Amino acid sequence: MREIVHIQAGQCGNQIGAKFWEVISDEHGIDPTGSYHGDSDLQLERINVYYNEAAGNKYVPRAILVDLEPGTMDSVRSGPFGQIFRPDNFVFGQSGAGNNWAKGHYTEGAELVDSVLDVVRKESESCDCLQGFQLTHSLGGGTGSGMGTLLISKIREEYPDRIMNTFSVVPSPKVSDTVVEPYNATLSVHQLVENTDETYCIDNEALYDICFRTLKLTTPTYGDLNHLVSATMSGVTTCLRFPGQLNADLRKLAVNMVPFPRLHFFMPGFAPLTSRGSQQYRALTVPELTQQMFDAKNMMAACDPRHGRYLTVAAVFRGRMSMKEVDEQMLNVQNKNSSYFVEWIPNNVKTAVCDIPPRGLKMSATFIGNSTAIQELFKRISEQFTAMFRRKAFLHWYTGEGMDEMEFTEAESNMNDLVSEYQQYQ
Amino acid sequence: MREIVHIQAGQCGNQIGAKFWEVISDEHGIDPTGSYHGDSDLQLERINVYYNEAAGNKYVPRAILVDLEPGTMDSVRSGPFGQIFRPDNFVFGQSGAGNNWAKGHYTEGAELVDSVLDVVRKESESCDCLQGFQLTHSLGGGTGSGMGTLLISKIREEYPDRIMNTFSVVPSPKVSDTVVEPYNATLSVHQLVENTDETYCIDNEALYDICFRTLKLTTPTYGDLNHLVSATMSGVTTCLRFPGQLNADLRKLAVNMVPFPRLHFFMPGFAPLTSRGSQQYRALTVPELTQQMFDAKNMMAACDPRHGRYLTVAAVFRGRMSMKEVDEQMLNVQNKNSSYFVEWIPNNVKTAVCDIPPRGLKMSATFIGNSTAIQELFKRISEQFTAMFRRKAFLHWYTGEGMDEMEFTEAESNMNDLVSEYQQYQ
Amino acid sequence: ADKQMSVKEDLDKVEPILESALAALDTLTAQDITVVKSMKSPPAGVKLVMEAICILKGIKADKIPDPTGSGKKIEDFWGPAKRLLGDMRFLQSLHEYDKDNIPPAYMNIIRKNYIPNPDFVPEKIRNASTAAEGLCKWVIAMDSYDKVAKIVAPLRNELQKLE
Amino acid sequence: MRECISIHVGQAGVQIGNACWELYCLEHGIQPDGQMSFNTFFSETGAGKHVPRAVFVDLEPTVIDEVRTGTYRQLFHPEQLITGKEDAANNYARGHYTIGKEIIDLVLDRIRKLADQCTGLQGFLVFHSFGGGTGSGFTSLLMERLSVDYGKKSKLEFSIYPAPQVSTAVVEPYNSILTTHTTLEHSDCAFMVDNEAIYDICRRNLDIERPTYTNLNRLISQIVSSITASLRFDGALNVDLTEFQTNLVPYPRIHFPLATYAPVISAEKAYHEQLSVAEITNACFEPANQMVKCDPRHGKYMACCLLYRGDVVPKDVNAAIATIKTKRTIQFVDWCPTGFKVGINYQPPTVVPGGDLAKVQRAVCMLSNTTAIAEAWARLDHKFDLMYAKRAFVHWYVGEGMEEGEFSEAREDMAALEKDYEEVGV
Amino acid sequence: MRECISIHVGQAGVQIGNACWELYCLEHGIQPDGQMSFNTFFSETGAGKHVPRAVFVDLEPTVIDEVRTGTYRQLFHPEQLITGKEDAANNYARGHYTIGKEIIDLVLDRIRKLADQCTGLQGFLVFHSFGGGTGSGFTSLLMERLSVDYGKKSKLEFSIYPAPQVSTAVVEPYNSILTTHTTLEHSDCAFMVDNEAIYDICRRNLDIERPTYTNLNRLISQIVSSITASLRFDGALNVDLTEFQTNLVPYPRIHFPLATYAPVISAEKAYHEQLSVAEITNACFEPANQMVKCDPRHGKYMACCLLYRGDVVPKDVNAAIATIKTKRTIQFVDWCPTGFKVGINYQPPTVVPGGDLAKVQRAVCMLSNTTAIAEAWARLDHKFDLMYAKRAFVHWYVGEGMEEGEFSEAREDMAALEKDYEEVGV
Ligand SMILES: Nc1nc2c(ncn2[C@@H]2O[C@H](COP(=O)(O)OP(=O)(O)OP(=O)(O)O)[C@@H](O)[C@H]2O)c(=O)[nH]1
Ligand SMILES: Nc1nc2c(ncn2[C@@H]2O[C@H](COP(=O)(O)OP(=O)(O)OP(=O)(O)O)[C@@H](O)[C@H]2O)c(=O)[nH]1
Ligand SMILES: Nc1nc2c(ncn2[C@@H]2O[C@H](COP(=O)(O)OP(=O)(O)O)[C@@H](O)[C@H]2O)c(=O)[nH]1
Ligand SMILES: Nc1nc2c(ncn2[C@@H]2O[C@H](COP(=O)(O)OP(=O)(O)O)[C@@H](O)[C@H]2O)c(=O)[nH]1
Ligand SMILES: [Mg+2]
Ligand SMILES: [Mg+2]
């Protein structure tokens, strides 16, 4: 029971999703042909969540692939794990959003949504009991922002009682990649704040930091960055998919992580983040993992944590460990970082222990933090956006698609509202 | 017992019939030579319905082939399955109807009918117990409309107590093929309404839709369209020909499907409609099949179902399934389509479960719907016709054959009568 | 002119109830409403209140698929409510709603039962949900304002004729 | 000896028969070959073989053809298996007036021959369906004939009643009502089971997720076996067919007892159970375990009978009954204080190879009249009223030797019945 | 006989159950198979395989799924194990109002069935957690239902209380308080153990550096075994469930005894020890050995009870108690002079293979009510006040069928409780 409906929108969404599926496949013993060849019974105990099995032990993800262009999703198909996806999943048009929110939401993507929603409906009724919808969609692109956001809205109208979680890849102010990245992000966020229960905000900057420093990969492939995010999402959903000493449902995490309706944004991490052959100087222990997780170098978000205080924390560990050890370990942690844990909430941390390791690490962990500090990320984008709006810049592309200045002003208001609330609960 | 006398009239009738016979042959284990080489005893348990046996295990369809021209029926002969017919069963003249109703009914076909009726009489007397007459005849042609309709009338006079069912291929307003298609259809329908118990209305448009979208054949051969209709008719008559958990006679279907004398027109479908390798992504279940059947893409009629409400429904499934599953499944369906099931009749659906699959699909289904929506099909043709009658167009071809304006007015009245009745029971 | 001033005094007497409707619009909190609505099945009182909002909006209750027990399809107004609330600009839409543009049908539904109900009365709603206070107030105040448009608007038009 | 006659009518009847005669054989110890005091249901042949004292009728030869090829084939003497030309096609007017008044006389012949065999002809059992075409008119016709012939003899009616929700056939509602008009004034007793309730029982208590007709049928058949075994076997308190009639019919008009067989227990549910005598009594009185879609609490049990089998000791039974009387919930009628008869038979039920049930040492078929069945009557009256407002499918019936006025009178009768039950409840 | 019911609710409850039913089996001599007077906790089934008189409920199916595959599997009834769709996700408003008022009725059914088995139903044991989602609302709901049903019957509550320091879940504080509101006015007695104190006991007395949930649980379970064994076994001074209620609850409202099992002694600590009767008494009264994070010296032992097992001779016990009374440090409440009951049971505790403890000939579970638990109440009231100042996570609960006012009233109740304890101390 409690099955999840995956979604991948935009090149970024589509590629992280690509690597994401591959990752979980290996975790559940599924090979490229959609056949099971795993020695762990526990994999197929709850295969349900992430895979719909058919005739002859074919195993197929509950995943919908959306791209306003054909190309990136055709690369998907060519890919090794691409064959496990269905054509039913591959739903595309042939007009590119071209990093325009208005193309994604209003125009090109409004034409392609109904078809996608039909596939959504196919995938909802095929569920024993639908739990949630995971959407991997960039904030700063065209097919992630507009098309992604539109998809979220309609889906929430259809199934309002269910979980909507989005591992949304956000702009990094220091490494901007696109023109109107500010425009895309701001318009996206305005909608996202109101349309999702939880959003895991991952910027490329932080990923690079991790790769360079810790994993010691000074040639990051998008593959490597993707591999990172993939493992993050796996960890989030391990509990549903495997037995545990304490088991955290997606709703459980949300409920434990959220002081208020609005402030649902999070920073995921992972441990152990080490290079190959940089594990022999180490020894895998609960303290080790916690220390790694609570370090700034192992945050997959823009904000430095220490520029604020974690409102809440939820550390979903994996592999075979003493609850006592974890308890005792994360009590110390509460005490040490007195400055960086919010007062409002005692027992800031929330520890969930899945009994399954990630097939090759004897222990592992996955952080989820809600920090007041992430206000800084929003500030950066607000600033970037604001300056360009002062010159009414790039306006013509958006006004061309029906969008209005007042909308943008309202999107700015949304951003302002988000940052003030964090300040209040600093 | 309960044997059926097939008929094929006009190129269209003759060709669907061609493919139809081939289809059933394979279902009953009969090869091109009229010899049985099947491993299923059940095939020859009720071979009767559709074949006469003679000396040396002869297998002869009780089918009469009619064409006012020799050519299409000579192609039949040349064909692989063509040589299964007893050559005495091809009754032809050498003057083409040339898409003239008046040539088919009044003139050229009145000359060739008596000979055909003699062959009809042969067949009726060779029956252990005649059940019905299946006529595959186009509405919009010359040899289907006039000649077909004339054949129906005389046969009904001869055997009024028996079943007359006609898988009549109708005009598609969006893909007109012939000049006076309106004229042919309107004159045909006028007669058909009063002369048949049940008529399965199949337009080429819908077939194309199926092929293109679902079967993913973007090169439809008339072969493929024909293969479709063929399977439809097989499904209709599976019950008579094979044992079942609940068995629906042709009369049974008619009786279950018809609220009133007149509104006997139907829309057939089929499932599972999938492309090769497309099937893959599906997994054959009762719910799957029902969902496919009740989808608009798997309707072999012009009308969108949702532009109206099904008066009645009769889903004749095939292969080995749980009556409970079907029952429970189609109860949900009643609930889901609250707006597209007519109130008058509770238990709108009628489930019949044949115990025989169609030799290569573990499960299968065949829909028969009576929708108020099909009024739209009649409207389109009425409109098309009416405009041309306003200019008294093409009149000379028909007046030349003895036909009169008043007749046409009366045919218009027939059409009007058909559409009003559906409106009343909307 | 004095007659005009008298109708404008009528309005001044009515201005607080118009102000009450405005205050109801205001009492629509940022995202507490947004979340009480995000949650599936809040206190029935608030479910009545959002049903009242649905009627206010003019959106009709749908039919729940009939259970085995009962042939009749259950009358459900919460699903319309679910979609109505779901709208991102729903709160904005409440702010946009006009007293003049109120179905008299809605007043019939709401005033009679919902306006004089004890659970629907703000005190119980204050208990029921802090977020719902606004919503209940909104429905009540909207009805009072359509009570008020119905009585003062034709009078003001008659006054305009006098003017 | 006390000896009986079986009459399976319609597809439903015959299918149940297929199941029934399996059971009896397994119990009495007869092989399908007929080779081995069973007097009641087997008449011994010349040597070795035993022949079922049964009648097998269907207008649809399809059904009984399956009989003729089954392993249950040589068990019957094809004196029994009667065939008709064409099926009643869910028309009551074909079952009664047309195809009935043709083959009925042949059936009356076989009946009479079988009657002559019986030294002590006890009575009859008539497996039909209120809502098949065959069993709706034909059954009534047959009943009428037998009443004229015998009158005094015992007549029983295992009637597959329409499930208020579950859908088989569109005209189903008309058929039931016409059957009731005619049946209630012939059959002294009528145990009515609907499929939906049986399906409920299949899913819940036996944990079976695919309820086939076969399994549902075995359950139906075991209900009879218990009714019989008092005749078929020794033991304390043995009941007779006449005894039910006498017991269960305080008012000569109302005789529609519900049945319910417990325990309904799978291979698992064997263990983690104690199968005690009093356990099984409670189970029988359960609102869910009823074989109709009726809640017994929505009225009063008027008279009840319980037919314990296997290792049942009367003292155990008497205490359970005390308990039952104690519970105020389970309402009884004011005017009859003790509304039970208890029959204890040393023979336990013996369960069919490849089936639902496991070895239950104790079992009990409770045949209980209630005023609560008046709910299922009302529902069906309503379904009929709705369609007969429109006068739908009127044409089929009328043209087959029926009266429109017959439909009106039938309802009147139903109103009277309902009124009677209301009186009784008061 | 005196016979009992087990109810494991929530993940915590079920885990404890997993441990509990192991122990009982090892004691009574039952295998996991169910094969071998244990009347109290095993109901000897017909087939044999003595099966527990237990109920196992969780909304999170994950937990009980682990049960269904464990070696402890064929021990439990199919009925024993009940599943829900989705987990309460640390919401009291989902445990009580939503998913509770759905599956509760099914559970009430199983309870009632089990109730019927018991000749002499003694009472109930309810393993839940004040601070899980399931066990916080659902438990309260269940309790309420059972109070309405039985009332007079005995109800016991092994409540995993929040450790003031140790962290599991963020909303944990809210849950406890809502539970208390409802629980205290149903459960006549509530033995509350927090994990932190148990962990302390694990580290110090057993020298275990990795306290897993399993080990903590075995300790929790042995506390019960002693409470029961007076029912389960022979011996002088045997106590009953009702006896605790009566003896330990002079004031009806205050029924929160602490527990403490000694000796808590490893394989080593067996030697370097002689385990005398009076040694073990002192150990029980130890401030550190308490199973709660409460210092007993910070108030007065209101009432005490001691449940010696194995080779205990009363004279030994009486002298130890004299000694204890002598010590002026260990304070007792004014109202009662002699605040002990002593139960001596000839059965010694028998320890679980692969576990903490070694063969202790003598053991004693002291269930001792003190005013000192008012410290742990205050702490938790404070935690709640802090978060409810902010009104944090208010949204989750409200939207799930709750009252904000319920939170206020709950505190009021707590204030009253605390005041009562203060009065008692005075
Ligand atoms: N238990 C059971 N009921 C059946 C079975 N087949 C049909 N029914 C019921 O019978 C009714 C449907 O009509 P049938 O009984 O098949 O019809 P018939 O009496 O054979 O009449 P014709 O088909 O016209 O010859 C409904 O009440 C069905 O649920 C079966 O195998 N088992
Ligand atoms: N002794 C013990 N306590 C546990 C265990 N698991 C959880 N707990 C305690 O239970 C509370 C945490 O919530 P759970 O009991 O897991 O939650 P639940 O009752 O299953 O509710 P849901 O998870 O929402 O279904 C805290 O008090 C934990 O310390 C366990 O295995 N043993
Ligand atoms: N982590 C990650 N980010 C990517 C990848 N590909 C593109 N992106 C980011 O996506 C952002 C642009 O949005 P994109 O979704 O490509 O626009 P679209 O193609 O129009 O949807 C850039 O900031 C890229 O850094 C990838 O494989 N991994
Ligand atoms: N489905 C189908 N339709 C056909 C085929 N051949 C012709 N038709 C249709 O038949 C219609 C014309 O009638 P036709 O019977 O050919 O006229 P005739 O040759 O004078 O009888 C056209 O609308 C064609 O689409 C075929 O093989 N399959
Ligand atoms: Mg039949
Ligand atoms: Mg849980």
Image (cartoon, coloured by chain):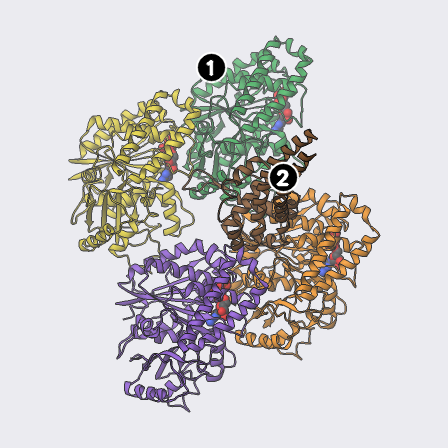
Chain colours: A orange, B green, C brown, D yellow, E purple
- Residue E152 visible in the shown view: yes
Q: Is residue B376 above or below residue B336?
A: above
Say which of B202 and B47 sits in front.
B202
Q: Nearer the viewer, mark 2 or mark 1?
A: 2
Q: Which residue is mark 1?
A: B157
- Residue C98 visible in the shown view: no
Q: Which residue is mark 2?
A: C10
Q: Is residue B97 above or below residue D132?
A: above
Q: Is residue B372 above or below residue A411?
A: above
Which mark, by number, is residue A318?
none
Picture coordinates of residue E376, whole percent (x, y): 48, 74
In the image, taking residue E168 as reference, residue D416 lies left or right, namely left
Crowd around label 1: few <14 · some 14–19 · many ≥20 (10 Å): few
Q: Secondary structure at mark 2?
A: helix
Say which of D337 and B231 sits in front.
D337
Which residue lies most toward the front here?
Answer: C2
Q: Secondary structure at mark 1?
A: helix
- Chain letter for mark 2, please: C
Picture coordinates of residue A404, whole percent (x, y): 76, 45
Kind of residue indicated by mark 2: Asp
Picture coordinates of residue B379, whole percent (x, y): 61, 23
Crowd around label 2: few <14 · some 14–19 · many ≥20 (10 Å): some
Q: Is mark 2 within 8 Å of ligand 2?
A: no
Which residue lies most toward the right here?
Answer: A391
Cα distance between the residues tagged 2 and 1: 85 Å
In the image, taking residue D258 as reference, residue E106 lies left or right, namely right
Q: Quadrant of the C terminus of chain E?
A: bottom left
Q: Quadrant of the N terminus of chain E?
A: bottom left
Picture coordinates of residue B421, whole percent (x, y): 52, 22
- Chain letter for mark 1, please: B
Kind of residue indicated by mark 1: Glu
**What residue appears at the point 57 percent right and 13 percent down from the top-left corner?**
B410
